[PDB]
Image (spheres, coloured by chain):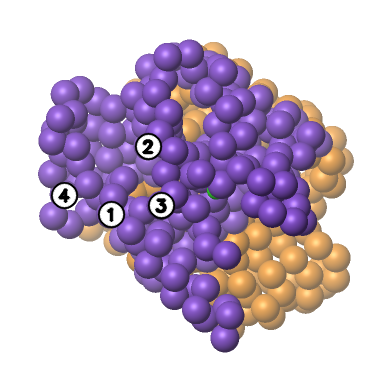
Chain colours: A purple, B orange
Amino acid sequence: SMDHYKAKATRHIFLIRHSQYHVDGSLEKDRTLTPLGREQAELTGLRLASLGLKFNKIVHSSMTRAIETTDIISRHLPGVCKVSTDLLREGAKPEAVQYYEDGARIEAAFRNYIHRADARQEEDSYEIFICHANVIRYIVCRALQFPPEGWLRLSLNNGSITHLVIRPNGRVALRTLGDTGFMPPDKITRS
Amino acid sequence: SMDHYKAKATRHIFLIRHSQYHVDGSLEKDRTLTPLGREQAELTGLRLASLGLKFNKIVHSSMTRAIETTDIISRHLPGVCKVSTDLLREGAPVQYYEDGARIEAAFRNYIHRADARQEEDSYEIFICHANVIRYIVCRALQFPPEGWLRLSLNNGSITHLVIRPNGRVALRTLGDTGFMPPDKITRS
Ligand SMILES: [Cl-]
Ligand SMILES: [Cl-]
């Protein structure tokens, strides 16, 4: 649950991990989805469209993998606005500096997108965020008031759907985590 | 992760919540699956069988709703041994102290206990109720057990924990019913 949180209606937060991608592309623009990754994103779009929900917004990382996952999923959700954000990117001892930076960035995403309620919300909301495993796991554990170690102990599939429900008083329920039940096992990957 | 734990191989723990059942049934023998519940169990059985895994065991609650969910799922898993246990039974929706103690006992007997005989990676199914599944997840991951009620598990859902030999635990999915059509999904 969440301290100092007050929103006007319930929020349904769907956190989608980007699909399988070419980790070894030289430049960020080369780090596109794999053919399997494109099929994963089709399955995720099919699933989301099948829920009978009107989504308010798709917010997505500006990394190539997340833009492409979004391009595919959005075809299934005609009329839903898309917002690109650099805040949901991952940055380029190296390890410690990178973790320090990533910590700040994932907390920033939490505060900006999850803890921050919109004063202009007028009904229950259904919000899609397409991004990466660190920020998704972190948001889940942060929202549920789990320990700082905790997010590293989750492991989420490519194209997976995580559903958090946030009540106006800040009560949080995790309805599903890392759901790829809608994908055949021969399409399921972690990277 | 878990302290005082050394296993020989990795264990894949699949925690399945019983399907939808008749909550108002008078006696425990009347609290059977609803027709939709039988449908949910079939979907969960189909999903489990599709994973290409030879499951080592199916451990289930001795409650009617769990026995019935198991009956259906086991049809999809021929040859897999089944063990009934009262350790996974739930009490009513200060007797609650002993129900609490029993979920800890369950965690200890089934999850924290590794088999010295198991030298190969194992795949273990537990079919039981939302309270003990949520507790197990929190305990295995060293989350505040009071976190338990922040987790919501659909009927017939699959929750998957991975336990490495050194006791490191990963949560791979929680409350997965993505294999069920939306109109078949229930929480009670
Ligand atoms: Cl991303
Ligand atoms: Cl049960």
For the residues tagged 3 and 2, is the chain the same?
A: yes
- Asked whether the beta carbons under mark 3 and mark 2 sit within 8 Å of each other, the answer is no
Say which label, 3 or 2, has the lower sequence index. Answer: 2
Tell me the residue that label 4 is attached to.
A5
Task: Decide: is A102 above or below A65.
Answer: below
Q: At numbered mark 4, what does the secondary structure look like: helix, strand or loop?
A: loop
Q: Amino acid at mark 2?
A: Ile
Say which label, 1 or 2, has the lower sequence index. Answer: 2
Outermost bottom residue: A93
For the residues tagged 3 and 4, is the chain the same?
A: yes
- Camera-side residue: A17 or B112? A17
Say which label, 4 or 1, has the lower sequence index. Answer: 4
Give the x, y percent position of residue B78.
84, 35
Tell me the residue that label 3 is attached to.
A87
In 3D space, how far apart are the residues under numbered discs 3 and 4 (Cα atoms)? Answer: 21 Å
- Camera-side residue: A81 or B149? A81
Tell me the residue that label 1 is attached to.
A111
- The residue that appears at 44% across and 38% down in the rendered structure is A84
Q: Nearer the viewer, mark 4 or mark 1?
A: 1
Tell me the residue that label 2 is attached to.
A13
Q: Nearer the viewer, mark 3 or mark 4?
A: 3
Pointer 2 indicates a residue of which chain?
A
Pointer 4 indicates a residue of which chain?
A
- The residue that appears at 64% across and 31% down in the rendered structure is A41
- Camera-side residue: B188 or B21? B188
Q: Quadrant of residue B117?
A: bottom right
Q: Nearer the viewer, mark 1 or mark 2?
A: 1
- Residue A139 located left or right of residue B173: left
- Asked whether the beta carbons under mark 2 and mark 4 sit within 8 Å of each other, the answer is no
Q: Nearer the viewer, mark 3 or mark 1?
A: 3
